[PDB]
Image (spheres, coloured by chain):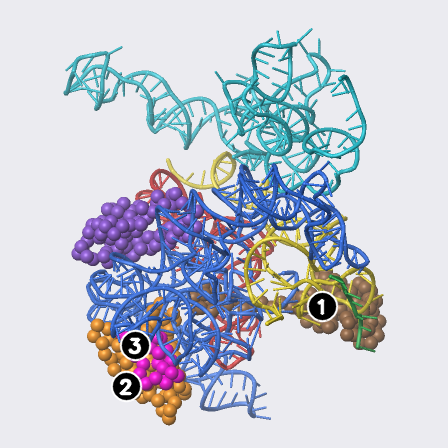
Chain colours: A brown, B purple, C orange, D cyan, E red, F blue, G yellow, H green
Amino acid sequence: ATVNQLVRKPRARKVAKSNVPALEACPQKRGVCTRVYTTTPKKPNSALRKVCRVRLTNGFEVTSYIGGEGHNLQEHSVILIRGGRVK
Amino acid sequence: SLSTEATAKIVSEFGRDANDTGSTEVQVALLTAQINHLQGHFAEHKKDHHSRRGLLRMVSQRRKLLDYLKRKDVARYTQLIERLGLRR
Amino acid sequence: SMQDPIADMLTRIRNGQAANKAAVTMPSSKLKVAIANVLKEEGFIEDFKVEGDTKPELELTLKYFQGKAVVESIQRVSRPGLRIYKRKDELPKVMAGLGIAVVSTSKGVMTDRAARQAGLGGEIICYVA
RNA sequence: GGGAGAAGGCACGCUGAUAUGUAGGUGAGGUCCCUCGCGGAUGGAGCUGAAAUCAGUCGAAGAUACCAGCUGGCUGCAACUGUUUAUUAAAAACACAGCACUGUGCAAACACGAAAGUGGACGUAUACGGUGUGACGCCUGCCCGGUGCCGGAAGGUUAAU
RNA sequence: UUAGCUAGUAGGUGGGGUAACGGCUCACCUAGGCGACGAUCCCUAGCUGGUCUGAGAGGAUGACCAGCCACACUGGAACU
RNA sequence: GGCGUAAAGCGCACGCAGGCGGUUUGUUAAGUCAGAUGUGAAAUCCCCGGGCUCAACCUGGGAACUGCAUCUGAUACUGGCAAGCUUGAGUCUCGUAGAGGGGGGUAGAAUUCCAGGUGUAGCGGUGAAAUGCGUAGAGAUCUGGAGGAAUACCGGUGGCGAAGGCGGCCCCCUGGACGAAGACUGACGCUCAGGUGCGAAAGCGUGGGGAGCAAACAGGAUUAGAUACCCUGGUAGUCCACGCCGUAAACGAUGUCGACUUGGAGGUUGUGCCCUUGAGGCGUGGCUUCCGGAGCUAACGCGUUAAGUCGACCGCCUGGGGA
RNA sequence: GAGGGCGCUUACCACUUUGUGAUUCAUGACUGGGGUGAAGUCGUAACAAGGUAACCGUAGGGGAACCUGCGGUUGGAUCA
RNA sequence: UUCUUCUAA
C-alpha cells in the first residue's frame, strides 16, 4: 500500500463477468427447442420442474426454465428467453 | 588476523597525521591486508560454514567499506586504487 | 534511520501530551524553531527554550488546560515520502478552521488563515488541533 | 554435442570496365648499416595472381560433358564404431564400455604340463580369474519348499584299519 | 505464461527527389539504433469536446451535436 | 483498507538499479508559490436573464473550461552547487564472554562383535503370549580384543550465530558481539525489484564406512478384518568425502532501521564509585525472561524487545471449493 | 534539327505459387482428476488424551480413508 | 490387552 508500490503497480480493480453469457449482452434471444422434459430440483424442494433444452441463434445449447403452470411446447419450436437463474 | 604492528604501519603508510585513523585509505588497506592474510584461510577452507559466513561478512565487509571510497574523491580515488592495485 | 526531524518532533509532542509531561526536549533545527515560534504565538505551547552551542537543543513547555491537554490532535501532512504543495485557494480549515494548519511558503512559516490574508500558497507541513 | 548437407531457395557462361593485373604473393637493380655475410634494413622494377562489382553479350539451357546425396513422416529391435557362418544367412547374433556376483594373500586363484616347469606376472586385492547382464535414464518386488553353494559339529550313519 | 528488437536499420558524406525539410531516395562510409520509464509481439479499438454515474475522488462511456481521422465491391496503381 | 491467529511479511542474509535522506552557511531558483499574457472552438453543464399560455424546449449575458505555453517575481521548504560541523555512520586502543566457525587429534562409559574362563537350563519379550534364542552350553558371569556412533553429570524459562543452527577435552586457523577510556573520520545513511549467497530433515549422485537404530520388508501376535498400533527380525537410510536438490508449523504463524512513551520482578554479560568494614551499598552499559499501567485490539492479547505513538523502504492480501 | 508517337527492354509492384514454421479455434477413440448427490458398499482417519495426541516437510508402503520412517511445530492432555 | 457404526423433514 506504499505509494511507490502503487506507482510501480496500479490498483487492479477486479473484473466481473456475466452469469448470463449466452445472450451476449442482449435483452432477449431467439431459440430452437431441442428437448422438453422435467427435472427434479436440489434438496430443500421436491417438484418436477418443466424445462427445455434450447438451441439458440448463436449455436449455443442451453437449458431454460418454463415458467407458469402448463404449456404447449414441442421440440423444434421457436421460443424466446429473458434470463434469470433458477436457484 | 592482522597484527597491531602491521596495522600501525598501514596507518603510518597513509598517515595524513600519523594519528589520523579515519582515513578510509588506511581502512581499505587494512581489510585488504586482513583478508589477503585470510585468502590462505579460505582457499584452504571452503566448508568454513560460519567462518565462510565471516568470509562473506568480510566478503561484503571489505566490499562496502570500499563503497564510499568508491565515491570519495576523484583526485584521490584515482591515486589510491593505483597504489592499492585494485582492479576497479 | 533518521528520515525526518519534523515527524520526530510532532510525535514527541504527541506522546508527551498523553504522558502528561511538562517539558519535551529534543535537538533543535532552524526549521524546528520556525515551527515552535508559531505554536506559542498560536497558543498551543507555553514556552520553548532553544539552547545548545555544539548542538542546539529545543526544550518545550506543554500547555495543559483544566488538567487535561490542549493539543487535541497533531498530524503530518507533507511526509518525506510524499510532499504536499497546495495553492492559496486549497489551504485547508483544520476542524472547520478552529484548529490551524502550518504552511511554509516563501514568506517563511505562518498559519493558513494568515497565508490566505497573505494571498499566497505553499507547502503544508502539518495539522495541529 | 547434435539432429542438419534437415528441409527449402538464389547465384553460376563469355566480353569489357573497375584495375589495359585489382586484392595479394614474390621480388630485383638502387640506398644505408655491416662484427661485411651462404648479411641486415630500405627499396621497389619485374613476374605471378584471386575474389567481387558494374555494363555488355550467346544459346532452349553456362555446377552444360565426365564427375557428383532422392528426400519426408511413424514404429519394431539393437545404444553406438565394430565381429561372423572362406563357398546359399550380416543380422535383433557376437563383441563392447558399463553393471553385479564369486574366487584369490603370491610359491595366489587358475591353466598347460605324469613331471620338472611355464603362463598368470617381473603384476600383489584401485590386482587377477570366472560367470551373468550389456551404454544411458528410471528402476529392479516376493518365495530357501526344492536343487546347488556356504557355514555348523552335538548326535545317527560309516571306509580302509 | 510477449525480453530481446533493428541492416536503410542508426548516423554521416555525396548525388537524386519533393511545394517544403529529412534513407524522402541512392551511393559510399560508420556501427550504430532501440528496449525493463515495456522495446518487441499478441489481443481489442476511430479519437476528443462530451455523455452517464458518483458528495467528491473517481468509474464507465463516445448513438444523436461538434472537432479531427479513416474508408468507398476487393486488391492495386497513377492520372488530372 | 489490511497482513500474531479471520486471505495476507519472502526461510533468512547480502546488494545494484531504485526510492529515501543529519546538521549549518552561501549560492542557485529547478521543484514549489504568486502575478501577468496567450490559448484552452462552439455546443453542453453551472449562474443570472429572456422567449414560446407554462413546462420540456429555444436563447442573451456571465462564470467555468480544473490545463498548457510564455514573461515577471518570490525564497521558507525540497532539490542543484559549493563550503563547514559531529550527534548519525565508520576506524584506531585495551579488554570481555561465549555449544560462533573450519582443520587435526584425543579421551571415557555404553552398545555390538570376536575369543576364552566359570557355570546350567532356560533366555528373551507381552496385557497375555508367540515368533526368536538356548544343552551344538545360551543367558548370566569374568577376562581379552575389535569396530562404529554419540559425547552422562555439568546444563540452566543458559550461551552464540541473521536464521537454518551449534554441546567431551586439546591443538591450529578463523569470525562476530559488547564494554571502557580516548583519538579520528566527516553524513560516509536507510531500505532494496531484479540479482547473489546461506539454508533443517528426508531425498539424489559417485565414492567410503556401517556399532546402534531403523522406512520398506519378514515372522509373531492382535482383531470381524489388521497391508496398523505390539513383539522378534531386518535393508536402504542414519556416519564420512565431494557435489545436486532448495523445500520445513524454516513460527515469535509478528519484514527491515529509526525516534517517543507508566512500571515491577528476574537471568546473563560488562564497567565506575563507596571502606569489599562478608557473599555489601550506590551507579552506569549490553542482552534476555516473566508480570503488567496507559494505550491498542473483533476479542484473545500485546504491552519500552509494542500487536502503543510515529517515521522510511520492501514483500503480500482481496468469499470458499476448484488450486 | 530537336522533340513527340508507337514498340522495345529495364526498374518497382498487384494478382498468384511454392515450401517450411508459428499461433489460435474446432474436433478426437481413449484417458486424468475435479465438483456435485434427500437411499448404496467398504472401513472409521480427524473433532475429547477421538480411544496409536495432532500437523508440517520429505521418503516408502498400502482397496480406501491412510500407515510408517526422519526432522520440526503446539495451533496437544496428564502430574504425593 | 481388546472394542465399530446410527440414513433421509
Instruction: List the residue tagged with mark 1.
Output: A29
Residues drawn in magenta: C7-32
From the image, state whether disc 1 or disc 3 is nearer to you. 3
Assess whether residue C8 is covered by the magenta stretch. yes
Give residue G71's position: percent from left, percent from top: 55, 56
Tell me the kind of residue under disc 3: Met
Label 1 to label 3: alpha-carbon separation: 75 Å
Instruction: List the residue tagged with mark 3.
Output: C26
- Identify the residue at horizontal 34%, vertical 72% (top origin): C4
Give residue C6's position: percent from left, percent from top: 33, 75
Tell me the kind of residue under disc 1: Lys
Closer to the chain start, of discs 2 and 3, is: 3
Assess whether residue C58 is covered by the magenta stretch. no
Q: Secondary structure at mark 1?
A: strand
From the image, state whether disc 2 or disc 1 is nearer to you. 2
- Identify the residue at horizontal 23%, vertical 57% (top origin): B21
Query: What chain is tagged by disc 3?
Result: C
Instruction: List the residue tagged with mark 2.
Output: C47
Answer above or below: position of D77 versus C90: above
